[PDB]
Image 1 (cartoon, rainbow, N blue to C red):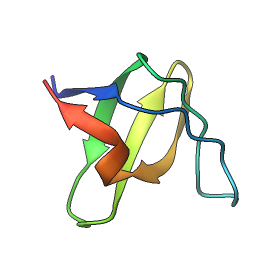
Image 2 (spheres, rainbow, N blue to C red; image 1 turned 135 degrees about the vertical axis):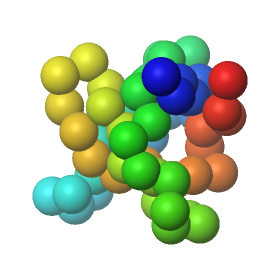
Image 3 (cartoon, rainbow, N blue to C red; image 1 turned 90 degrees about the vertical axis):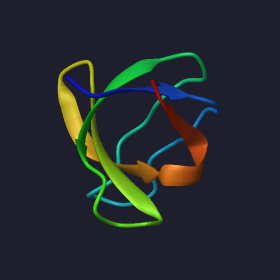
Image 4 (cartoon, helix red, strand yellow; image 1 turned 30 degrees about the vertical axis):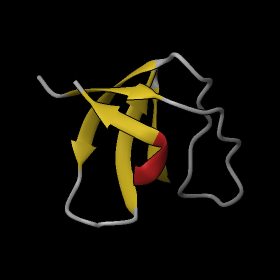
Length: 56
């Protein structure tokens, strides 16, 4: 498993993005990009800014 913690709220702005709330625990799917990481947030998958999450 690889979990991350949402440090901030983020509202999706494009079709490949997903929304998260501060304090959400997300499943990390792909962290190859330095700026945008692919995560699973409940049942949805998509990108959020890498700077806004913290690896656990």
